[PDB]
Image 1 (spheres, rainbow, N blue to C red):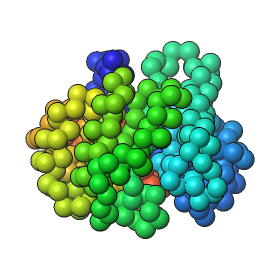
Image 2 (image 1 turned 180 degrees about the vertical axis):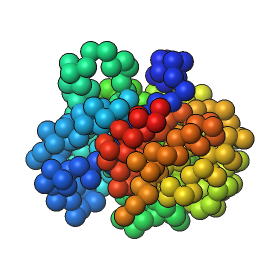
Image 3 (image 1 turned 135 degrees about the horizontal axis):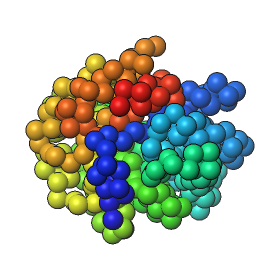
Length: 292
Ligand SMILES: [Cl-]
């Protein structure tokens, strides 16, 4: 039931996509909001689909949905209730799946393509950059009330797995890993923001974070994302010594074909899911694909 098994027992590496903001703004979207996904998903759903399609064309084997900040908590500020919010969250999956369908028409040989439902941290709902600090404090029960509607909406709309990403807080991580056991068929990767090579943003030694996630077979991969490019390889090599789960790495771009240069380094550090975060485009993926 591991959706990675199809691809990883055929290739050492699989490619994720990259930032969506970048090609929405080149397509003419103004996003000066943290709840920008609400407007686009409603006003310009097609643009999001087209961004997914472009990453697929560029070599991406997995779309990450536009749900990073699509929570009932977040969208309540736009006067949307939980069910209105879940319909949007689910739309983000449908859009990525209609993109995938479109890409298979253009390329019948393309192989297995995945859709990962994006699950942002609580810090991304607090518009403060806390997702790279994790200096927030909630009960496990509290994180779970936060995450559940999105988790159900992502799964109900057909995500092949959840992308639990940009995670700074160890308590939130355990809450999320506890939450997923309520949905036995769900599979997820857990990806973290760091303070350093050996620690989560909040301070937790990565040893603790792995020992925990080790006990949840639903967590089918883990690693790091939205990390500076220069900080990726040290973190990976440390993870690599704690787990042989497939490792995940998608860092910020180097500037502002070079993120792509780390490929060999990462793969040797056990990385098997590779893509990009802030400031990346389909160009970064095409370069990864060229170097594989
Ligand atoms: Cl993005």
